[PDB]
Length: 603
Image (cartoon, rainbow, N blue to C red; front, side, top):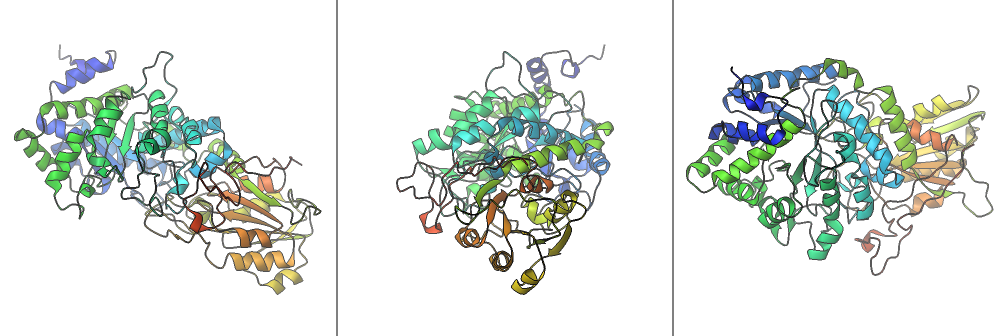
């Protein structure tokens, strides 16, 4: 009697979208296109402005140490306000779950993408997607801003660790993260259609379209570009695989292509992504991406709104000054500068994702899913991935030496040393807990030191010293040492050491340790770094990348429970002045080529 087609779960998605669209006011439409930060959200804001989406930016948590249930109650509170609007359109909540649900205390932290590239195991990455979706849904969140399918072309980029590989083929194969996050698409599926299986899955986001991994001294992010076969060949193809796997959303890059800002690039956003690849999900801006169309950023926000919406973006990550966004966009439509057909396309796409994923049927969090956060099975998977990510670069100083690895679990006394041996924050790197990475015991996990202690025979005495001098090591009576050093957490603009040399003490500790006893050096880094001095000092050396919360992945290999199988997913340069230098370059002169990796057999 009071039947409303869009509220009927048995109806086809396109019919529900059209029925809802046709009822909506301009305010309700512009609302759907507006994404706000939880920090500026209140029940009245969300209801009075018909807000479509919320996010937590990096570090935007309801409180320090918040439980899964706290997150659920936060998201539900916001949802209750949205469901109380006239039309009852549920909001979608997004977050950077890029190596697990990494903003959340006690979430499993998976290896960062560069390590996952070293695994060469798309099925492992899919399973990581599955586990990640469960941990995101544990916190009531429905949308992950992942995968980053950047093809990082210069390791000086502060986000190079979020790229699976300099080789776009490895990136294309790791798009299997998508069906992990979202569920596998039906048999008869049309490429470019959005898909999410239901309430145990999340919407995904291929980002950042396009050419975010492209060059400029640190691909570091202001035009990071190239030319047309730069494009279609290196930076674009994985978006097609993303389309084939029904990625729900695509996020636009801050960078430029051909001197046109991606956030204003109608030819690529509308002409190529939507009209040629046939993408039918929604296009989302990056954080104040529209603001940055201009220089200085934010200096003509009227133009930002116009240029981005006419380019074809559907949802704007404002994320704070929503009043200005809504006001300016409303004026533009009222004035006929942006046609209603453009608004209606954006809203169509937003709603299409929402209906397809089951959001109208399950807008609230499932309390029974709370226990998925940091669930042990997920940690076991993270430990497998960490172990598979490790690249053995050296296992003996001369061809006549006994291989150091695997180490024996039974020895009278052993040394664990280095700034990175008992620091969970470092082991995890950036995008962890989160207005950056951090240092120590920032979440639940097992450091390298804790992993060693968990692994060795009860008779083995384990001594920790963060930065021992040469004489302490010589005098200690140690059978061997494991020494872990490397990079501090960083991102594109913060903490990014462009000399690619690890901070001291790091090398000095490796030298003091290895100068006194046979040593296995575990290098924690987001990328290749200057390594010759570390190699020359070390009996064995392992590139462990940023392996996440499960440090037992490292010891599983060091002690021979499994063999080393990882292979470099990037070129290891001899020198920073060779860069950029990627596989296929004209004077390809690597220290270690892409694909290099020594192996051991399980003991």
